[PDB]
Image: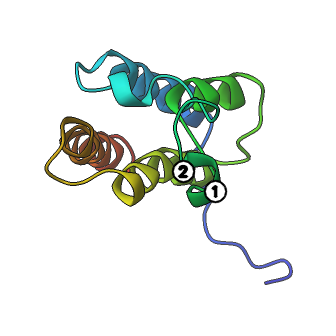
Amino acid sequence: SMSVKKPKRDDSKDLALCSMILTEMETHEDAWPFLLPVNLKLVPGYKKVIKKPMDFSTIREKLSSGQYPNLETFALDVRLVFDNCETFNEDDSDIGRAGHNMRKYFEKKWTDTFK
């Protein structure tokens, strides 16, 4: 509360470390469904159904331009990419399986880097 603060967690490396995680997600072999925004002219249903589209390139541009106020807003956009994927793709599809694999990969890196 006013003039009463928990000890200051060092957040000065968060930007660099989220960049590194994002590089590792970009270079994973199952990243291909997630590298670029879904083409809303060419994929019937996507625009109406997926209210907040997100992809790795969009996260990379937001990261690079100071549009994440803290490491939690960064994790929320990464998870959004996988939540969108599960909303639109059957579990038993190449893209569905890609999404589950990438979410697992992300969540381990996240825990090991920050928890």
Q: Which mark is residue 45?
A: 2
- Kindly report the distance in space between the C-alpha atoms of the residues bearing marks 2 and 1: 6 Å
Asked which secondary structure carries label 1, the reply is helix
Residue 96 drawn at (x, y percent): 24, 46
Relative horizontal placement of residue 44, taking residue 41 as reference (left or right): left
Numbered badge on residue 25: none
Q: Which residue is mark 1?
A: 48
Amino acid found under the numbered disc labelled 1: Lys
Picture coordinates of residue 67, whole percent (x, y): 77, 37
Q: Residues within 10 Å of mark 2 (few under 14, many from 20)?
A: few
Q: Is residue 5 left or right of 28 when viewed as pictured?
A: right
Q: Quadrant of residue 1?
A: bottom right
Figure quadrant of residue 54 = top right
Q: Nearer the viewer, residue 106 or 93?
A: 93
Q: Which of 46 and 25 lies nearest the eye of the viewer?
A: 46
Check disc 1: other Cα within 10 Å, few if <14, some if 14-19, many if 20+.
few
Residue ID at (39%, 20%): 26
Q: For the C terminus, which image quadrant?
A: bottom left
Helix, strand or loop at label 2? It is loop
* One can see residue 111 in this view: yes
Residue 30 as seen in the image, left or right of residue 17: left
Q: Residue furthest right?
A: 2
Describe residue 113's horizontal placement relative to residue 105 as left or right. right
Assess whether mark 1 and mark 2 are in contact (beta carbons under 8 angstroms): yes
Q: Which image quarter: residue 108?
A: top left
